[PDB]
Length: 125
Length: 133
Length: 195
Image (cartoon, rainbow over all chains, first blue to last red):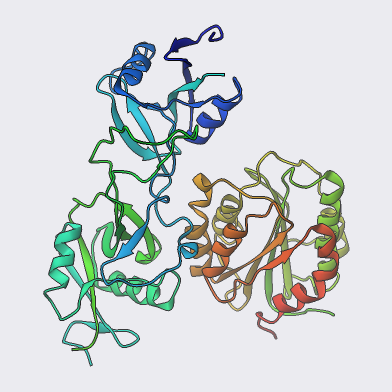
C-alpha cells in the first residue's frame, strides 16, 4: 500500500511534488523518498491520465518532469559526407535535454534539464 | 585550386552561404553546388574547426546565431532515450515534434566553433563542403 | 629545479568532499612545493590560488605585494570545506571572467593548473568546452591534473582536446602528486617567455 500522500494505480504509487528543481535534482529527489522510486514513467495512456489527476493544482500551460533524460546524447549520429568518427570524441556533443509533460494534453516537451519544474515520483515496492 | 568563392582547407573546398534554409534544404543545395558536396563536416577538435569557425565569422555578418553543418541524429524515433530512469523500456511516447532537435549547427559565440543541435525545420545560413573539381 | 619566467600561474584546487580533509592538506602541500620552485614576483611569476566547489574561494590573487613566503603561508592554511560538489566548468568561468578578465601582462603566458579530484554532472560539464575555449581565446592555457579515480576522465579529456598546450596528468591520488612536481613544474615552465 502506498505511503501517505501517494495515490495508487496498477500496482504503483505516485506523488506530485510542487518542488522546483532541475531534472537531476528531480530524479535524485525521488530516489530518496522510497527505495526504487524515480521520476514518473508513462507506459500506457491510462497511466498518464491517472498522473494527470494528481497534477491539477498546477497552472495551465506548465510541465512536470518525467523519467527521461539526455535524449540527444544517447542517439547515434552521422554526417552527410559520411565522415568517420569515434563516439568517444563526442562526449557532450548535443544538448543535455530531458522530457517534461503537460498534464492537460499530455504532450511531452524535450527541454534543457537545467530548468526548474514541478514533478511526479513513482515506485511499487 | 578551388572554384571562385570556395575556400580551401587540407585539399577540400569550403564556402559560406548567407541564404537561410532548413537543414535538408541546405544539404541539397550543397550536393548541387559541386560534385560530392554537402553541409561541411568537422573533425570535432581539428584545426579544420578553426578554419570553418573563422570561415563563417569573416563571411557571415550582422547578427545570425547559427550555421548548419552536415551532422544530424540518425535516429528516427523522436528522441533517443530507450529507457526511463527506472529501467523501464521506452515504448509509449508523446514528444512534441517541434522540440525535436536532430540537426547540428555552429554557434556564433566563440566565433562559430561551438556545436549545437537545433530543430531541423529552422531557417539558418550555412557552409558547404566538397573535394577539388 | 627552478622556474623564473613571465608566467601568470593559477592553481585551481578541487576542494570537494571527494578528498578527505587530511588528503586536502596533501593537495595544499603540493601547491606549496611547486611555489618554492617558482620565482614568485610581480615581474616574474605571479600566482593566484582558488579553492572551488560550486563557487570559488580565492586565497591568492596574481597582483599582490606580500612576500612569497607570506604567500606560501597563505596557501598552506587554505581552510578545508570538502564541498558536496566541485564544478570544474564553473571555476573555469571564474578564471576566464575574473582572474583574466583583463590581460595586463600581454608579454607573459597565462596558465591555469586545474587540480581536480572529482567529477561534475553533464548538465554542467556541457559548459566545459566553451569556457576552456574562451580561456583559449584569451591566451590562457589549461593543464588538467587528474587526482585519482573520482576524476572524470572524459571531462579531463574535454579540457585537453581544446588546445595542444592543454596537457593532462592522471594520478592515482594525492600522494602521487608529491612525486609529479618536477614533471608538471618543468612542463609548465617551458611555455613561458623570459626577460
